[PDB]
Amino acid sequence: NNWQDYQGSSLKPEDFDKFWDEKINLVSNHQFEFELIEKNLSSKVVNFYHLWFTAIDGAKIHAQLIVPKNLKEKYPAILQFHGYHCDSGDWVDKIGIVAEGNVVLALDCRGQGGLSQDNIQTMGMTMKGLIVRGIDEGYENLYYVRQFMDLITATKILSEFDFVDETNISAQGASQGGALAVACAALSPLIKKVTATYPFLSDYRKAYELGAEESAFEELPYWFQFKDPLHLREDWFFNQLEYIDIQNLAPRIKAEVIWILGGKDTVVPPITQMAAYNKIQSKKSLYVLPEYGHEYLPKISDWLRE
Amino acid sequence: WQDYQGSSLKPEDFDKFWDEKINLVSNHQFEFELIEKNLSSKVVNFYHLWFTAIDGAKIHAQLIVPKNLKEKYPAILQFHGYHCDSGDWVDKIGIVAEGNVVLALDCRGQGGLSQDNIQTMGMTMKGLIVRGIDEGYENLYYVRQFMDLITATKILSEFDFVDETNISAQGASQGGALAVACAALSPLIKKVTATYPFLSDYRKAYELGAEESAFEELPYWFQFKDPLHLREDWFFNQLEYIDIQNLAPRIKAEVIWILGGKDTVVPPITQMAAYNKIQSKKSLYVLPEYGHEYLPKISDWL
Ligand SMILES: [Ca+2]
Ligand SMILES: [Ca+2]
Image (cartoon, rainbow over the protein chains, first blue to last red):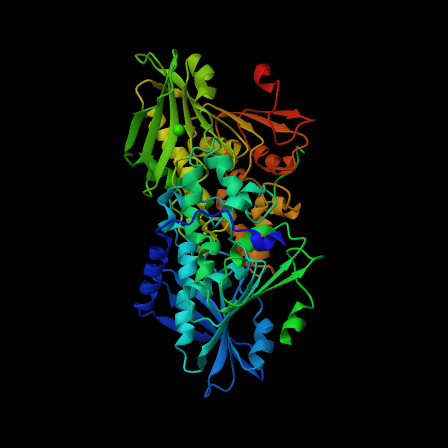
């Protein structure tokens, strides 16, 4: 019941919206060069393509493109994002949803398990963690600033396909993928639907307050342990992360939201995700599996088919 | 433990590769700068030492000097552990008060002030052993980190108040590995005191199951970049160039090797791959009840 009343712990800066408005404009006015190279996997109902484009910062970004065989008609499209450390997953995992008449764009995050390039440069700590990668040069140099812009760029390219129904584009993902799906719908309001599973990257100040050494937010106490153990720049540190806290993007969402989480999740605490969910103002639904944690959630996928 | 020969597959080009890097540093005039540290002491002065490496990165070190300077002093290069920095300035007051010069080097991008400028198309999430491995061993993080050791030794020896004939190196874990590597790439070093050195016997460290050790990056890379082990041979062939057991034979300094018997962070078997290949005067000290932690009593004993 209190999850409704949790307003979050963020300190949204006045300049937040101007920053992201400018980034949206930059993507819209940029003509992106991309390339499609078919991957050799034999199927009777689907074709597979490597999608390579150059981001606004020069980095080479990779995505999985999975399309039906008949391309003479337009299909609804689904943007799918993956979890921390992982990649876009097995190609065959997309055969079912595209066989129903959909186009899937599975984006690879920069410098993780996939093929996308990380080109963040910094004078500070590069040992571990991608939330704080580049934090010394300010929020403008944060890794997720470019990672969020890849979502807008992927949506732009996906929307301009002659076989993609631009009116029915949706986003889905788990953990980090849930955060990126939420950010993708907020930064590209054309998105019609979002299905986010225990989204990450939310309420950094609260995630630190809970004690994050065993959570997915462990890089935050790690940074203080080795970069600022006396907490001399605590305010400055969390002020940079405000620009990549998805709860600050949540109000801008116009898509329908389906939110799924596990009640025993200690990797991504439910309280930090509710900071973002409570600030969604469009149509939203919240589904909980009490006995499950940061893991595969059964049955819920059949429930939503209805 | 004496007869363990290591698991390395030393590449044909290994010595030719590192000989060129030593020559490159030896023939290069490095630009450095000294900036006063505000720490107040009656027996020592503290200085920020900033130099630019041959690759452009800005490298930082702590320089701690006695108050007098008209005569030469023995010098000590000191290196730190994984994730850490050069430590508190006051930790060096005692050793410098005895008439020594301490250069405490900060590793690149590891919590200290030194810059990491490795660029790669591959995984940047975690780990500095495998940082830049996709572009080959030339782009490995520790190739430039090892050259910083040679460069730091170069600058330290060229001070008019440093007795270049009595330069030694010390460190623990990563610092122990860098201390060992420092002696191999600069044989002028007279003494090495290495405490449970890291960065040795990568193939064996993986074979033991490294998920709970300091080598966890190696299974991590396979877990997310190559789960079917399609490039296992290529992976460990790149790491040969930064395995200190391959550098150990060229060491001429006397070596003091200290380790803890219960160490699961850096298993002793990987350390012995490097220690057994040292051919100069060497001694081995073991604390059976201690692990990867502070080792008492041994400092007084020496
Ligand atoms: Ca592939
Ligand atoms: Ca300082």
